[PDB]
Amino acid sequence: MRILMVGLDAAGKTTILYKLKLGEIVTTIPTIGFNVETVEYKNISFTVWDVGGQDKIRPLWRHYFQNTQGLIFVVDSNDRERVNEAREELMRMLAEDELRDAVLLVFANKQDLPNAMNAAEITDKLGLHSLRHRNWYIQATCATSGDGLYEGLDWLSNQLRNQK
Ligand SMILES: Nc1nc2c(ncn2[C@@H]2O[C@H](COP(=O)(O)OP(=O)(O)O)[C@@H](O)[C@H]2O)c(=O)[nH]1
Ligand SMILES: [Mg+2]
Image 1 (cartoon, rainbow, N blue to C red):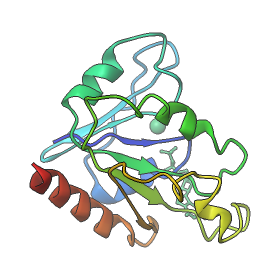
Image 2 (tube, helix red, strand yellow):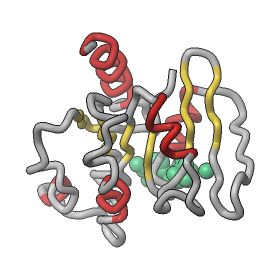
Image 3 (spheres, protein in one colour):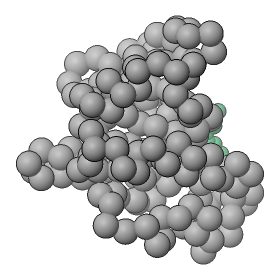
Image 4 (cartoon, protein in one colour):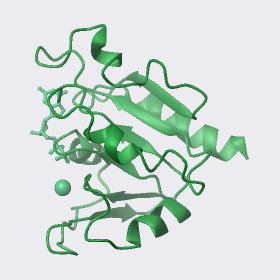
């Protein structure tokens, strides 16, 4: 099954995967620049990738959103420099029908980081403090140890299957 674990560059995508261990990741280069890591094997299927509009205008993203039922948002809580880079992509995932119920799994790892915004504004400059109604979920995620990952994956799985 497919859950699009979206996230910026160096957020934590490869680590989470390092744990799950869906087998050496085939990191090929589809479009001049746009790389996608089809980390899809067995029950789990993660079409890995990064942000960037929608490549050099190709309907592959749409076909992903259409068939996908999952939604794992990994927010480099630290990257406070490009902060809105997510909001920019998310911009489309706003109205999009294909991904209505799809539970957005806000894995907010890298919060305790000295660089990142102070403790309180952690969930501020993100916009997840006021944005409600949308289907989402956010718990303290520690990929290194493994914490955060459990509650997230389980909650998502249950919600999606149960909601319908
Ligand atoms: N200090 C520390 N480093 C992290 C954290 N989690 C992962 N990183 C490291 O940051 C780097 C980028 O993560 P990576 O998995 O390669 O990200 P991806 O590029 O977005 O797939 C790797 O060197 C990770 O080990 C964390 O919260 N604390
Ligand atoms: Mg990669």
